[PDB]
Image (cartoon, coloured by chain):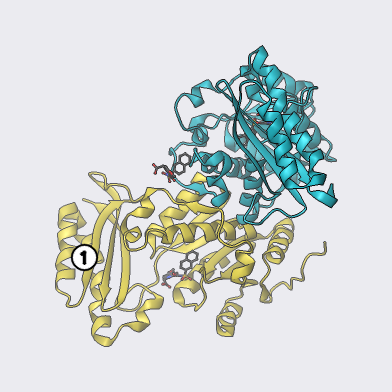
Chain colours: A cyan, B yellow
Amino acid sequence: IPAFHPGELNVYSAPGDVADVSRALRLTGRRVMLVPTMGALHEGHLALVRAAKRVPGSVVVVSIFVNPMQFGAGGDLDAYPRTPDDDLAQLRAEGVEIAFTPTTAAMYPDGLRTTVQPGPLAAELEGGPRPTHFAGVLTVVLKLLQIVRPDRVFFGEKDYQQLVLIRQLVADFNLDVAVVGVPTVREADGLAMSSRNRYLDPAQRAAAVALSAALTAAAHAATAGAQAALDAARAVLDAAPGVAVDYLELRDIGLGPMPLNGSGRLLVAARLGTTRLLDNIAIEIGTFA
Amino acid sequence: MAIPAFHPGELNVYSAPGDVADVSRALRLTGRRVMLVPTMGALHEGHLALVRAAKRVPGSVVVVSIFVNPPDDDLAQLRAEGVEIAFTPTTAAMYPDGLRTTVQPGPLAAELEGGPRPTHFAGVLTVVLKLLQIVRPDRVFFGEKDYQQLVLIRQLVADFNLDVAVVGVPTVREADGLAMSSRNRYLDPAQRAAAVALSAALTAAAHAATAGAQAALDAARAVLDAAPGVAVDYLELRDIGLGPMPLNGSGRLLVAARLGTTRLLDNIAIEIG
Ligand SMILES: COc1ccc2c(c1)cc(C(=O)NS(=O)(=O)c1ccc3ccccc3c1)n2CC(=O)O
Ligand SMILES: COc1ccc2c(c1)cc(C(=O)NS(=O)(=O)c1ccc3ccccc3c1)n2CC(=O)O
Ligand SMILES: COc1ccc2c(c1)cc(C(=O)NS(=O)(=O)c1ccc3ccccc3c1)n2CC(=O)O
């Protein structure tokens, strides 16, 4: 097995290197925590890392891999922010002991061949116009889970549909891993952290606060019912300059095929110029609020 | 969080996935190597050879799963083989949320057997994946008879970075060479006699192969052509991964045919020239 220096940041590229280090550590009693990222790390990722570090005796593995198989288009792949120098420095600052940074060739030596086919949830919301997008995400996440074999894996709640689908993958394939959702870290005005916030110009940045403002307005309006909660969110989005709403949807917490009851999740997707932003919040309807 | 009861050297039967998962984890912690033999029950000699191959690994514990993917005699046989674990889940236990996330095979699944049944292999790979995740065996054993199935499994294991060794076990055959299959019982005596042409064609090919690929194929085809009531669906020579056969070297020759209502398959290692 490769060298592993405790208390230091150890960087592995070969899947076999991280797998052997991981297994060795699990056998010596350390619980392995996985934080899978596409790099370009911000405070929301550091929140994921901090949550993983809280687990007694853990060793934290952060993966950084921009997965070509979840991009469609159209230069989306080429466009994705890459800032690997900032990434490793932050990990060192947080005392993470393993970074896993595989090559595309090591992840996909045979190209795309066997893949994960998500359930019907993957065709709706974000997946409506991107029909293979979530097959790309679940295939890579399955691979990462098999390579690292973590006890727990950590995701932000901001991409909530993705989180739900990952929980489905875990249940549906009997994966022996705990999925931990971490609440979305926000800028001080409530804007959800995101890699893509860097694409907002000053005016778009100012308008973008409408997404989180609409969602919290809805969560408080919801004592008056679902209609009022949705109408409040819609009004705030409507008042915002140059915000173009894609969808604004209220669903059950698992995102359907069940009607909303007392507790739910309100999801919004909107374009500012060319930048697509997503956010969501827990909603309690009526009495539960 | 007490481990379910396990009595070493007895046949222990579990229906709950969580239970066999806890036991297999407890066993692996104490040194034993976990071996998995997936079956659909109605055990025959082919299954017993998979069991015998698994039992010979030193330190092995053998898990035999019995699951019909949508009797006490099976268990008796497993007992007589010294198998310690039978995993016998219900459909509901395996699919508590119904059909949802599934495995999509690569394009090999659309070829050969995937012609009459284009979603067959998606089903097989999904349930094999789940069985591997529940039991987490060091090694998993399949017969070579369903060769395309086997290759698709090794693609699954490679593609998803699974940490199991896939062991293909030579096909058990009747005395005249007919490959073991649960379907052989349905053949009336005329069909049963004609069915020997599949294996006869493939062994003839494998010996003709010193004279090259075309000789091997023409020898198999002549043998199939000497049999009445044997409607050949395909007869193909491929490399060992089921891609195109290289100009020489190692390959596999596969056949499938219908006799009355029964579809039969067989295959064989071929060495060119
Ligand atoms: C706890 O607070 C937060 C808040 C926002 C977060 C996160 C954490 C994490 C992300 C995020 O997008 N991370 S990621 O680009 O590196 C990422 C992380 C895991 C992924 C798994 C499958 C597919 C895509 C993935 C993308 N994001 C959102 C974003 O960067 O747009
Ligand atoms: C609803 O409208 C569409 C449009 C295209 C679609 C689909 C649906 C579904 C597929 C599809 O599943 N294609 S695929 O099985 O070859 C496939 C499957 C999984 C993939 C994962 C990551 C990237 C690409 C992937 C392509 N494909 C791509 C295709 O058939 O080539
Ligand atoms: C070592 O020699 C042999 C020879 C023939 C074999 C076998 C082994 C195994 C089978 C067989 O098909 N077994 S099975 O119906 O129980 C079966 C068949 C397909 C399976 C696919 C995924 C998971 C489990 C599977 C179990 N069969 C053929 C058959 O029984 O139809």
Amino acid identity at mark 1: Ala
Query: Could you say which is closer to the camera, residue A10 or residue B59?
Result: A10
Asked if B9 appears above or below B106 in the picture, the reply is below
Q: Point out the image quarter for the N terminus of chain B.
A: bottom right
Residue positioned 52% across, 21% down in the render: A79
Residue at 31%, 72% (x, y): give it. Answer: B263
Residue drawn at the location 49% of the way across and 45% of the way down: B159
| Location of residue A156 with respect to B158 vertically, above or below | above
| Residue at horizontal 80 percent and vertical 22 percent from the top | A188
Q: Where does the image place residue B138, in percent across and percent down from the top left?
A: 60, 55
Task: Answer with left or right where residue A141 lies relative to residue B69.
Answer: right
Residue B215 position in % (x across, y down): 15, 56
| Residue designated by label 1 | B204
Of all chains, the one bearing label 1 is B
Looking at the image, residue B270 sits to the left or right of residue B13; the answer is left
Find the residue positioned furthest to the bottom: B189
In the rendered view, tell whether residue A189 sits above or below residue B160: above
> Looking at this view, is A48 or A235 the one in front?
A235
Tell me the SS state at disc 1.
helix
Which quadrant of the structure image shows residue A97? Answer: top right
Q: Is residue A105 visible?
A: yes
Res A185 → quadrant: top right
Give the left or right position of residue A200, taking residue B150 as reference: right
> In the depicted view, which residue is nearer to us: B219 or A226?
A226
Using the rendered image of the protein, determine whether residue A4 is visible from the camera's viewpoint: no
Farthest residue, direction top: A202
Q: Residues within 10 Å of mark 1 (few under 14, many from 20)?
A: some
List x then y, in percent, for residue A284: 79, 47
Ligand 3 located in image quadrant: bottom left
x, y (%) of residue B25?
71, 58
In screen coordinates, is A276 left or right of A193? left
